[PDB]
Length: 311
Length: 312
Image 1 (cartoon, rainbow over the protein chains, first blue to last red):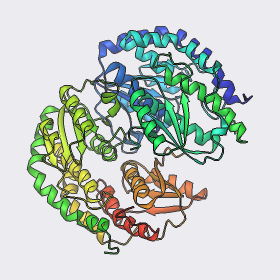
Image 2 (image 1 turned 120 degrees about the vertical axis):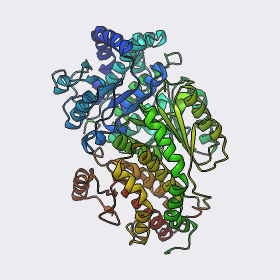
Image 3 (image 1 turned 135 degrees about the vertical axis):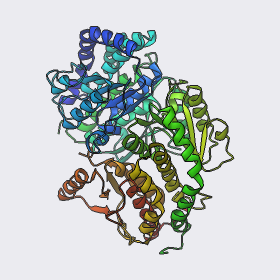
């Protein structure tokens, strides 16, 4: 099944919107890359919605693995409630916010600027006041965000992070990945569904397991299952997890992850597999392709469960 | 004592054991304090059981608020699965592990030491081979735990972190709060139950909400309820949450938190409150007093639920 939901419409527009984003942002991210190689960030702090920031979890793996620089999420309360200014000299702060207007986001941006960090904002609204606080805005270019469950705007956030990472590190592999990204998303949209409602009928509790980048995207999957399908879903590391949805990314984590899933299957668990739509996709793009496929799939699961994913 | 469980017995020893720990570790934490003031850590990275680690979440609030130094948890897979060594020069890395033997913890510690970081271990077994990798070992001095669910050993992790912060920063208020921690913990033990024995009859799903230090301890509370009570419990920030157990700390987070709880309750949620046992507990140790009270109470709750907390 396919659906006429706004959620699905936005999800299906992501590949083209991201192709346009990457082209339009190539110059600004290139220059930001030059700034970052000159500045030499000691760490990367992500400012958003705290530890519950899914983009921030993805960013941790991205910058730690590609740039070897420790990356972490800020705790909003430290700036807003406790009134602290941290010592962030020589650090890079990346603010992630679609609207660029929330008072807790603006307070954290101001504190980062006052602490001496070089400050970058990934924001969808280019006219937002965050632009007058931070050093540079990288526009997300996702267009109008009309659905209640975010799809394209999340993928656009990850594409911008990836492009920022490619330009900074100049890692050749990652540059090729970013160049292949729009076509890889389209291929994922055009592929056969990976998740079908039938697998979820009669499931009220669900554990989503992943490793590494797969863990980052499992958090996003668990959230959408709760938001759109009314299924109590929770994401865990397959390493730490001492009815299961297997987020199966083919990257360096695949081997250990697969073995953990084999363990849960042997210990008698009930498994639903989300495999990549292609077994030859670049590993750093694979998580985005899997989310791309899933966003389209979950609109149909909703409608199949009698839920209107747009309400 | 209100139950005959090993869990309660161990929990009740924490004030005495923690007083003895602070006494035994004064020299070593003082010396580390002096070294850290010269070294001037640019950040503090916590190595433990995933980017998850609960003690590490408490450590983030502590070092960022008291020392103004950015603090965060390591992601083990970055080192183990993705094979990466981070640029950690000028940083402090604190390895938190009761046994100090897990091959993964030892591997992360060698990576940190190779990466140029100053390394401290908080460990319970002083003979563990983590001692041969790190620069300084802070023994937890919790003794053995015969209960499946950690009580005194978790409190002892938090008190070691607090003592480290106190000796490093020398913030007078924190120094005083740490010196008086045993008294605060014993006051929480002598106070009346905050989570009543029969308060979770027929609750199968539960959200634990906190803010700031309260959020850090919400994580440990949710884990213990899953472990000892067989309740599907999950911790969230009351700011982000957008059947509820309220972790109510009377600190700078109080105003914002109290009105977030007021909103969920007035929109019809079943609320239980964990209030501080005393109004005047120093704010930074209030989270340990609340955990202390909770460890005794949850042993009784388990029993009321038909569970043996010593062997669930």
